[PDB]
């Protein structure tokens, strides 16, 4: 729901992204090395699953970005000359010296 | 191998007073392209029609530097199966290249480079998602 | 392997490939020219000028012979390329898995900065994240980019800031210009679980102290009539008894002994000076937020401080005069800060305005009281009401002799 | 005095989002609450109409007499320049502040009759010496009463966005050009998270 | 006679694929020469795939007229300047492979006997069933904004709503 | 406009995801189509060798493309505006009367007070 929460979910997707390349090679290894067409069934199903899980997962995010109405451009920061937590920060140490 | 060999005998040529359409096949007789099994051995281009089996004939003539020779199988006095083509160019005899094996070879040479080119470079760039593709 | 020397190898092979393909194109374009005119247009310029068109002929013929090893080569080559394909895919997975690992750590650290509500931005072309560490306040507000440290395999924030440590040091000086006492500004320690956040605080602390220094440095130029000198490294406020107050930016018990008592006093002086200096700069910062909603001269901060000092001094000189000639006097100052509800009020309280000093000096017990109302001004002040009239005086010099007139005949 | 402006709209649900984004980009906010009362003379000209304004953001709501007490300002809001696109709308406003014994009793003596009233409510942001105001016009409980609650114009009212910059002299060349030169910098800043086009006033 | 036209037409199809590949090769070189610092990896890779599609067409084209070509011999015509330049003739007609290609065959043949037909067809019949397995299984998953229309209708009604409130603030129309 | 911007960012993101997910599936299939060898000529297998390698390389680059997209999305989730600023450890809260006393104590240093008259 929060912005930091949605990043934590991407990190989840990301963990499973390199695995697309392993499960692909695994399929080739099944027929090329092990000659077993049923290991190829298993691993192709696995490869296609991880590929679909990541694809939809990311399209879910690109949409949830539009849902949260997150702006496109990195905006020019505002210049706060003084803030409520800085003032009492100065106030604390200045009393500590007196 | 005879496909990529260049046979020449300047001694015979010199001792025969140059090459002409009349002696060019007798010159080709000394070459490792010529088979002594052929109908030419026992035997003119009129007498070859009457015979059957392997026979060597001049298909094209352009003296004093070019003669195209054809090895062929005579089926009848009409039908004749061509076997392998040869040519005498500046008293040197070559075996006319096969259209396939010469094109397929050049494409095989060209494809070798590509693999060699790719394999080497595919290793060099390093990928970092934040940094993109960088060359170390 | 040099990146530039890797390019030559590539050009080489692609050029070997070209000359091979082109050579095949040359042969066939010559062969075709016999049967089509437009076909000769793919033969090399050199071949075009040196070799006539329709110079290559072809005849129906040959087997060609079938090769033994060639069919074993085809089997080998395919089998070898398909296993290499597995190795490569398994290699690329293994590296990219650890690549996502180091990326996971970097983003878990970045969430910590977002969790704390620190402004994070990306430069349009940089493709890297940056924190606005100068967030809370100060004159200049700079940003610092976050990166992976290549050596320690940890994280840090890089900045334009020229220093590691930066803090205002206000000190006092001898007649011999020796440090009689000093005060370097510190900061309240903020508990940080994140190494990435530790940096951000250190950086703000550095920038804020730089800001207060340059505002102080700017003020020094504006006030030379107080004999204030500056090297852009130090600020020297000449004070009484040939003493000096040296303001600078510092970068990279017994309780009853008279010398120890004096030293403690001078520590309190420098500490409060630093403390007020910071409060006054804070006020000036708040003033700029008001101005930004609609800067001239320099911030006030250094001069009101000078002013409040000279007040103690001049009123003390008066106390000496009145002591020298036994004169009973009552000194009643009403300091703006004395009645302040909170720190936001005390912030406004530290100002030369709303400052009056009431004096009731007694020439004799049998003579009327001379009421003196002292109100000095920053730029360029003594009202004396006696039995006869109210008189305003230019200087303390004049006040003192006006009292002298009232007493003398005794 | 001349007022150079740009108009946009923010929906009722996106107000908290646009204000939180407006807060994080430009210096501010500042609470703005005004009680407006319009008077028309005895076809019709909208420029000939007089528009009064009373800043009540720091005023007590239960206060009975405030028409002679709270500060009032006379505004003569004209019509913007015709045929304007790709650039900002420009309209001259003639300003005059007043302090007198009675404000409500004088205005009817001139020959001006009561037409309508609207209450401006929202936040005002500042950046580059040019102002941007995100407001909402509401209808009161009683006529000329600061007594809450305030009824909106519609069931789910949006938030009108007004970006205003001022140039006191029409004769000025660089001053008149700089307000338009800075509104490009404003338009580009809010365009990334908000919508602002040219609307006729 | 009838068959010479078939070879001619097939060679014109071959000549064309060789021309297109020569063009992509010149273009690849052109791109490499501009940066004078090994070009961006994606563009190097981009241009390799261009070659891939070009060689794939040529191998398929050569094998399409496999017999047609295998059954033809090239030699000079009576018009060739055989006197002055037979070494370029010999080069145009060079049948020999690149030394590096020869060594490749030699080494891949060495490794074959160093490690030391019926099962060759058996493995192939598996790769075919694998392709049929994948293409089947790919259709059991779905790949690749009416909420955008809901957010759009919000803008238009609020714009017409704004057009009505500016009239009330100036004239007073409810 | 802002809505068109939101749409365009989603569109470009989707497309780059789509082309990457396609390439992964397409190039993997391409390998399987070429994987067949029996009956093929050495001259016809040699370019297949390049193809098969060229394709696996493309597959990796397509996965790396997905990582470039996820990195954008993360940076877009850290570019959205937070509601408030960060708190501080103001703990060791200031004592106003400590400050007032020290201030007057110094301001009246060596001076005789009024007896609060």
Image (cartoon, coloured by chain):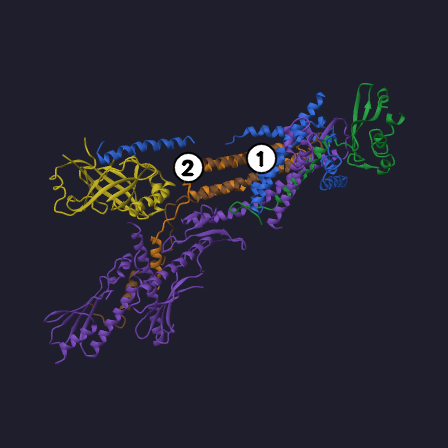
Chain colours: A orange, B green, C purple, D yellow, E blue, F brown
| Residue that badge 1 annotates | A46
Residue B96 at x, y = what percent? 76, 31
Q: Dot 2: few (<14), some (14–19), or many (≥20) neighbours within 10 Å?
A: many
Q: Which residue is mark 2?
A: F6
User: Residue furthest toward the bottom?
Assistant: C410
Chain hosting mark 2: F
Question: How far apart, in angstroms, are the residues tagged by discs 1 and 2?
Answer: 34 Å
Q: Between label 1 and label 2, give the one nearer the viewer.
A: 2
Where disc 2 sits, the SS reads helix
Quarter of the view holding residue C71: top right
**Horizontal and vertical percent position of residue D75:** 20, 42
Q: Residue E92: where, in percent of width, then height?
A: 71, 35
> Tag 1's secondary structure?
helix
Q: Position of residue D180 (x, y in %)?
A: 32, 44
Residue A75 figure quarter: top left
Q: Nearer the viewer, residue B29 or C329?
A: B29
């Amino acid at each position: 729901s929060s912005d930091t929460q949605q990043v934590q979910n991407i990190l989840e997707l990301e963990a499973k992204i390199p695995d697309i390349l392993s499960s692909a090679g695994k399929c080739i290894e099944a027929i090329q090395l092990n000659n077993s067409l049923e290991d190829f069934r298993k691993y192709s199903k696995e490869f296609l699953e991880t590929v679909e899980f990541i694809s939809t997962g990311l399209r879910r995010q690109a949409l949830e970005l539009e849902k949260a109405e997150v702006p496109v451009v990195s905006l020019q920061p505002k210049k706060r000359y003084a803030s409520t937590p800085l003032s009492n920060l100065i106030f604390d140490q200045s009393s500590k010296l007196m | 191998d005879l496909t990529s060999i260049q046979w020449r005998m300047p001694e015979w040529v010199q001792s025969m007073g140059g090459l002409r359409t009349e002696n060019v096949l007798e010159y080709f007789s000394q070459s490792p392209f010529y088979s002594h099994k052929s109908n030419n051995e026992m035997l003119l281009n009129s007498q070859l029609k009457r015979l059957t089996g392997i026979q060597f004939v001049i298909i094209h003539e352009r003296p004093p530097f070019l003669w195209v020779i054809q090895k062929q199988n005579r089926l009848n006095e009409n039908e004749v199966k061509p076997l392998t083509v040869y040519f005498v160019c500046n008293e040197n005899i070559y075996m006319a290249p096969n259209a396939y094996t010469l094109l397929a070879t050049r494409m095989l040479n060209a494809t070798y480079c590509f693999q060699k080119a790719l394999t080497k470079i595919e290793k060099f760039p390093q990928y970092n998602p934040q940094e993109g593709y960088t060359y170390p | 392997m040099d990146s530039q020397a890797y390019k030559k190898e590539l050009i080489e092979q692609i050029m070997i490939a070209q000359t091979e393909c082109s050579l095949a194109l040359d042969m066939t374009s010559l062969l075709l020219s016999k049967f089509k005119e437009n076909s000769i247009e793919t033969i090399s310029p050199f071949l075009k000028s040196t070799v006539p068109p329709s110079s290559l002929q072809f005849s129906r013929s040959q087997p060609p012979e079938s090769k033994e090893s060639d069919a074993t080569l085809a089997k080998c080559w395919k089998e070898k390329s398909l296993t290499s394909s597995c190795k490569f895919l398994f290699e690329a997975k293994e590296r990219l898995t650890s690549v996502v690992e180091t990326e996971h750590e970097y983003y878990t650290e970045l969430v910590k900065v977002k969790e704390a509500s620190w402004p994070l931005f990306n430069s349009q072309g940089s493709n890297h994240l940056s924190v606005q560490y100068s967030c809370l306040g100060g004159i200049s507000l700079g940003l610092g980019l976050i990166r992976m440290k290549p050596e320690s395999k940890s994280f840090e924030v890089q900045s334009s800031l020229l220093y590691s440590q930066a803090a205002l040091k206000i000190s006092i000086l001898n007649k011999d210009r020796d440090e009689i006492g000093s005060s370097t500004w510190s900061w309240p320690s903020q508990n940080c679980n994140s190494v990435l956040l530790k940096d951000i605080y250190k950086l703000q602390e550095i920038l804020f102290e730089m800001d207060i220094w340059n505002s102080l440095l700017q003020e020094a130029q504006s006030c030379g009539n107080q004999g204030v000198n500056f090297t852009g490294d130090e600020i020297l406020v000449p004070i009484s008894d040939d003493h000096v107050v040296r303001i600078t930016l510092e970068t990279s018990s017994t309780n009853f002994v008279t010398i120890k008592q004096e030293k403690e006093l001078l520590k309190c002086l420098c500490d409060t000076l630093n403390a007020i200096a910071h409060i006054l700069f804070l006020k000036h910062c708040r003033k700029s937020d008001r101005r930004s909603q609609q800067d001239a001269n320099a911030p006030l901060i250094l001069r009101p401080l000078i002013f409040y000092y000279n007040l103690n001094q001049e009123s003390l000189e008066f106390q000496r005069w009145l002591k020298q000639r036994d004169i009973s006097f009552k000194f009643m100052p009403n300091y703006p800060w004395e009645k302040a509800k909170d720190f936001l009020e005390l912030e406004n309280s530290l100002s030369i305005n709303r400052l009056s000093i009431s004096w009731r000096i007694m020439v004799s017990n049998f003579e009327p009281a001379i009421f003196i109302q002292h109100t000095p001004t920053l730029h360029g002040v003594w009202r004396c009401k006696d039995q006869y009239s109210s008189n305003q005086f230019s200087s303390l010099k004049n006040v003192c002799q006006y009292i002298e007139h009232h007493i003398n005949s005794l | 005095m001349q007022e150079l402006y740009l108009l946009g709209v923010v929906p009722s649900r996106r107000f908290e989002a646009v204000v939180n984004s407006l807060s994080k980009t430009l210096d501010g906010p500042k609470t703005i609450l005004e009680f407006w009362v319009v008077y028309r003379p005895k076809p019709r000209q909208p420029d000939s109409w007089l528009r009064l304004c009373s800043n009540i953001e720091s005023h007590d709501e239960t206060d009975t007499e405030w028409s002679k007490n709270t500060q009032w300002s006379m505004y003569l809001e004209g019509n913007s320049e015709p045929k304007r696109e790709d650039k900002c709308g420009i309209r001259p406003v003639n300003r005059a502040k007043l302090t007198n014994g009675s404000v409500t009793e004088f205005v009817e003596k001139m020959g001006y009759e009561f037409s309508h009233e609207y209450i401006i409510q929202g936040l005002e942001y500042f950046f580059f010496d040019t102002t941007v105001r995100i407001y909402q016009t509401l209808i009161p409980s009683q006529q000329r009463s600061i007594k809450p609650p305030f009824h909106p114009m519609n069931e789910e009212q949006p938030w009108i966005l007004h970006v205003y910059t001022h140039v006191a002299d029409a004769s000025n060349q660089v001053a008149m050009a700089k307000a338009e030169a800075n509104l490009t910098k404003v338009k580009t800043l809010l365009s990334a998270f908000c919508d602002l086009k040219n609307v006729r006033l | 006679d009838i068959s010479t036209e078939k070879t001619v037409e097939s060679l014109e199809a071959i000549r064309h694929r060789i021309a297109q590949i020569v063009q992509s090769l010149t273009h690849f070189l052109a791109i490499l020469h501009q940066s004078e610092s090994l070009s961006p990896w994606p563009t190097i890779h981009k241009n390799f795939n261009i070659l891939l599609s070009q060689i794939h067409s040529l191998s398929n084209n050569l094998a399409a007229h496999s017999h047609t070509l295998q059954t033809t011999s090239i030699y000079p015509s009576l018009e060739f300047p055989v006197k002055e330049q037979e070494p370029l003739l010999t080069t145009l007609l060079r049948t020999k492979a690149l030394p590096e290609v020869e060594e490749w065959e030699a080494n891949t043949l060495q490794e074959y006997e160093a490690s030391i037909a019926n099962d060759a067809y058996q493995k192939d019949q598996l790769w075919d069933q694998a392709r049929i397995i994948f293409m089947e299984e790919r259709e059991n998953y779905s790949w690749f904004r009416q909420l955008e229309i809901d957010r759009a209708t919000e803008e238009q009604n609020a714009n017409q709503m704004l057009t009505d409130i500016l009239s009330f603030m100036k004239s007073g129309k409810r | 406009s802002f809505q068109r911007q939101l749409v365009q960012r989603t569109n470009t993101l989707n497309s780059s995801i789509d082309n990457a997910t396609l390439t992964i599936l397409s190039r993997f299939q391409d390998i399987l189509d070429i994987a067949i060898n029996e009956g093929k000529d050495k001259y016809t297998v040699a370019p297949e060798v390049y193809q098969i390698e060229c394709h696996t390389v493309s597959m990796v680059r397509a996965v790396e493309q997905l990582l470039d997209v996820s990195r954008q999305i993360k940076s877009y989730w850290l570019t959205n505006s937070l509601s408030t600023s960060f708190p501080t450890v103001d703990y060791s809260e200031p004592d106003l009367e400590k400050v007032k006393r020290t201030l007057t104590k110094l301001q009246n240093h060596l001076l005789e007070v009024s007896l609060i008259e």
